[PDB]
Length: 379
Ligand SMILES: O=C1CC[C@@H](C(=O)O)N1
Ligand SMILES: [Mg+2]
Image (cartoon, rainbow, N blue to C red; front, side, top):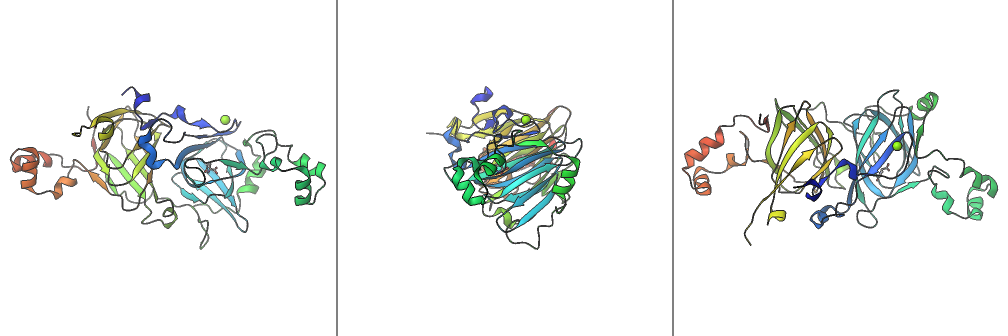
């Protein structure tokens, strides 16, 4: 596994900036099928990262993809402008927001020191996997799409003399993410509901955050929390989930597999060693290829459904990731070792036949791990 050969691994440097901005960046990973047809089952999805430096503003624009924004660091204000409604939310770490495709948005990082980072999942509605940005704001740089219209049409549309309206669209030359003044920050944020306050909603609801809830799976060595479409209606159309997994330093998540959901995992903190069992790269008779590697901040690992996987935190940091789940509804985590695992639900005689060893002996071995989900890693 020279890593560029592991098709499920997408190193951080593979994310491509969509523009050159002074106060931040917006970078997107290539289509998942760029180097392998093994990922054709998730071809319509793209993941990206939005970074805003302190005291910055990202210009109004919309995308042709249905998105889910997850704040991984800092605080920022998102304002959404529809044809007949305005919504603004003050987002914080852990917030999850479903953004309808075609929503014109702008972002503001009002903090004086901390960067605002968002991990984004988008699903195409035009050609599979193609998601583009449409800058309504802008002029020469970023180019505003209004410049695609002839001057007589702009004049008639805006009821403004052509030279004046043309001029409006050529004043901006600073780029897509620029400096915001302290006043401007106060002004643009301020109608923004701060933990959320969706409205007593219909179309665009506010963010939700699960970081204060009890983990679905947890132990002294790690935690797993997930926003499922079963619980959050805003995620049903995309049939996506947003998972948060943290493995404490020196810990590991016990081998497990997802029953039907493919996960696009992005590292937000730390480092980890991963090992996955893949029958495709390996395998008439089936053979499981040992797909392994190391993950660093910003890297992405796609975990296909049904594939056994384990992550081992390395060095002196907890290892934290945000995972987007595709085909999420009805997905179940199946652990392969630990007190709570699938073998708890397999009878003794079946274990004996499974491993050609006395059933009580197989059970004795499977009961040695008294902990579940996350345990101390090798050392
Ligand atoms: O689909 C996407 C890509 C970028 C993000 C946005 O509109 O900022 N939505
Ligand atoms: Mg930049």
